[PDB]
Image (spheres, rainbow, N blue to C red):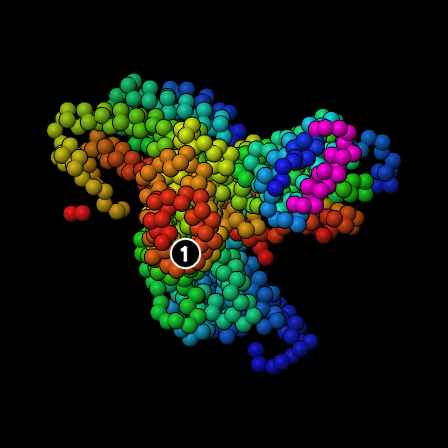
Amino acid sequence: QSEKHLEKILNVDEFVKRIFSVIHSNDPVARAITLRMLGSLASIIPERKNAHHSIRQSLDSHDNVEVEAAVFAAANFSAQSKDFAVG
Amino acid sequence: EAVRLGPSSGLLVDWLEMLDPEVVSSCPDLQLRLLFSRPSFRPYLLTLFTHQSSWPTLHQCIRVLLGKSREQRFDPSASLDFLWACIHVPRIWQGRDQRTPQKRREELVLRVQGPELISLVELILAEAETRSQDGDTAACSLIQARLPLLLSCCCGDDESVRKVTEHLSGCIQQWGDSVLGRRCRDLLLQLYLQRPELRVPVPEVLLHSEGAASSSVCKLDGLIHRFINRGADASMACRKLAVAHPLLLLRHLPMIAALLHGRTHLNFQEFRQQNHLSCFLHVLGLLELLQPHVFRSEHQGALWDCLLSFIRLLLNYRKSSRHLAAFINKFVQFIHKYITYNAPAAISFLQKHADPLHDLSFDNSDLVMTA
Amino acid sequence: SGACGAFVHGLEDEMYEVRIAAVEALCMLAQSSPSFAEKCLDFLVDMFNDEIEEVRLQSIHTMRKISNNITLREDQLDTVLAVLEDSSRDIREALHELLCCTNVSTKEGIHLALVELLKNLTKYPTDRDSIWKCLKFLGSRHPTLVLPLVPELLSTHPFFDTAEPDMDDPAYIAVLVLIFNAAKTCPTMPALFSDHTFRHYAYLRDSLSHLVPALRLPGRKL
Amino acid sequence: PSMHICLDFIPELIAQPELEKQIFAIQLLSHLCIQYALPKSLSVARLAVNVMGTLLTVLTQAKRYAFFMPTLPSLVSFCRAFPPLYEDIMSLLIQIGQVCASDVATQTRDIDPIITRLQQIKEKGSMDPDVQLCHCIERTVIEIINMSVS
């Protein structure tokens, strides 16, 4: 919802770390929510290689909602981040 | 199937998915001919039949397609990826952990019968003989790509034995030597397949499962030779694997020739315990146990000449012929290699012309000139 | 007829303005004549402990200009230690270009160079591109010398398969790209790989192509 | 994928006065070791081998049979997953075998599996429980040998 108030964040590294620290769990719904959150943040972190690797790994996962969340995050990170597009 | 409707064809495809829920519902022969024939909407209809047909109908289609029939009523180009999609249906793997199998042996497999697998391998080897513009390396790449499903559909030693014992005849577009040599991926220990591969003498870079054990044994032997209980399999298992499976040793010879390169550093050859007499004698015995492999085809000179130069450097840097049995064994091996083939001498003369000016004694002039 | 020296007595005699000309004549005579290198490489290596910022770079240059038909078994420690004594910001790239174009006799020198490059990385992460390029060149020069060292570089276990290293670690990506570059002409490279090595190669190859080459792994396609 | 956490209560499931709970714990640990390979899994497998070896001398024949009939494939999978345990398992097996060697000779039988020592395995009904346990031990040893050799 609050997308325009996203670029005015001072501490970005700690925020991204706290967001990404929950994608390593074994819960597919949690991983899907984390992927959707990362895709929602595709306007402030278009070069974080960890997010690209997570989206690449979880794109062909054995699930149904996690795959859709990975597709959404991949579209968001492919809008920007030419490197993610070519990858 | 008859009219060449260019733009409207897709419209007809709609009528194939609107008033026809199951593909094989009214007539099986016409649908099988439309799906698998001797066009453009083929992959879409294949995906529809894969993700919209019931399991009994799918098994029936699989058993009627992969059956023994020489009427060419099924395209193997579509049959291969159809089977690959039926094995990897996303409904079969719903929510389990992603990519955590056992690489030693796959448990979840698709069981098949005898004649079914026979017809499958027959059509696979038959369609891989066209080679319109692929060449030769692309055929091997396709074989390597389709080998996983071929090993997954059998999952048994009896099926592998039945597969390796079937060798067709002919001399044009054989393409069987590659499949017979691909047994190294399944860690096959059959002597018939090894004999067939040795008779074919086909050099292949296929990824083998038993190559890791051979590499580990070679590394352990090298470490034991460089350090001096680990010496048990260092000299007894290596030669056993060499006399049993010579292809693995021939393919591992690249990394073996790069070892024992400590002769240039220590030129004394009198103070070394085993780093200059054990590994050299071991590799000399390994080469002696492979007389039929030293005079083999090409793609092995890069290792043969390397081993020859290493032996020459070890003999020249010796403490004035500190070893008697090793020199005699090396001379006998060189004589046998020169008598078995003429390319070995033509390739080693460039080093012999310089090695004959170092000793200049009655020992190097042996081959340079009971019961 | 020659009854003089000026080769082993002209180096440690006076100021370095003549040492530079001496090593220049040395590399000039070694470039033309293919011989004479095996007996002058020792002298060219042992002249590094000269505590002069000029003779060091000139030694790097004369070794790079003669990096052909030469061997290196134990003379590497006297030529690699030029990066620990000081910063040498403008000499480090030359040393890395030298270490990649040369040949190594055994795997011990390869392991020494690798651990030294890892030390330089963990101590100076500001020149990782030069390290990756030199490792690429080293892997493309002689890929066989690293074959008996594959299970020793990366931490792997025959029956555990645990202790997964960090992805963005600048210490493991170097070894990964070195293995991938040495995996070109190796007969059976993936026979000793781990489980995550295949996905690491799949991610690095699709992200960058100037350092990771194309392979024929059974897991990948095309 | 959330089955590894069961390891954290596998030892607690072993220390139970019911033989069925112990058998189920041994089988679950066997499957977890053949699926997951971790040092903690190796430690729990070693503890299971120890508690199975110490239960051979505190159980009667009627309970020994029922406890060692299902739990031998567990040892087979432990050998398949953990090489360094081989010796231990072998020793354990030997012990159990010798125990059976004293149980068959006690009471007269109908098949006399003692003279069957000089027999080979043939690829691939109602009998005596001790003879059945002997045959199960022999079969599991054969499978362990075939897995380790191939």
User: Which quarter of the figure is the N terminus of chain B placed in?
Assistant: bottom right
Q: Residue at horizontal 69%, vertical 49%?
A: C210
Tell me if C213 is positioned left or right of A45 in this view: left
Residue closest to the eye, C2 or B87: C2
Looking at the picture, does residue B213 appear above or below residue D41?
below
Residue closest to the eye, B117 or C82: C82
Looking at the picture, does residue B92 appear above or below residue D1?
below
Q: Residue at horizontal 53%, vertical 67%?
A: B135
Q: How many marks?
A: 1
Main SS of residues in magenta:
helix
Q: Secondary structure at mark 1?
A: helix
Residue closest to the eye, B167 or A32: B167
Residue type marked 1: Ala
Looking at the picture, does residue B288 appear above or below residue B116?
above
Residue at the extreme bottom: B3
Magenta-colored span: C12-30
Percent x, y for residue B10? Answer: 66, 72
Find disc 1 in the rendering and name its residue.
B345
Residue D78 location, quadrant? top left
Magenta-span inclusion, residue C20 = yes
Residue closest to the eye, D131 or C12: C12
Tell me if C38 is positioned left or right of B216 in this view: right
Tell me if B248 is positioned left or right of D123 in this view: right
Is residue B207 in sight in this rendering? no
Percent x, y for residue B369? Answer: 36, 54
Q: Residue at horizontal 81%, vertical 43%?
A: A43
Residue B159 location, quadrant? bottom left
Percent x, y for residue B330? Answer: 36, 45
Q: Residue at horizontal 67%, vertical 48%?
A: C31
Magenta-span inclusion, residue C140 = no
| Badge 1: chain ID | B
